[PDB]
Amino acid sequence: PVFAKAIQKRVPCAYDKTALALEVGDIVKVTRMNINGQWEGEVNGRKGLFPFTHVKIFDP
Image (cartoon, rainbow, N blue to C red; front, side):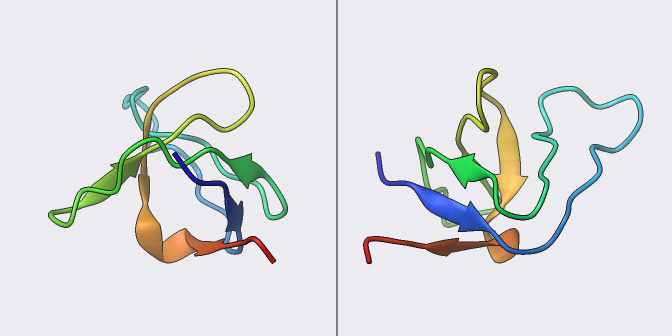
């Protein structure tokens, strides 16, 4: 994968749960970067989907 850094909160749509909950400063292990929508990653623990827009990649 690659690790990205959450840069904009993202409250899972109540009644979603595939949707990753994101807090700023979370480490997202982007597990899949679908060019058509959300990415697959696992914010500390659970896998799940998320907007690529709320993260920034980091090396540094």
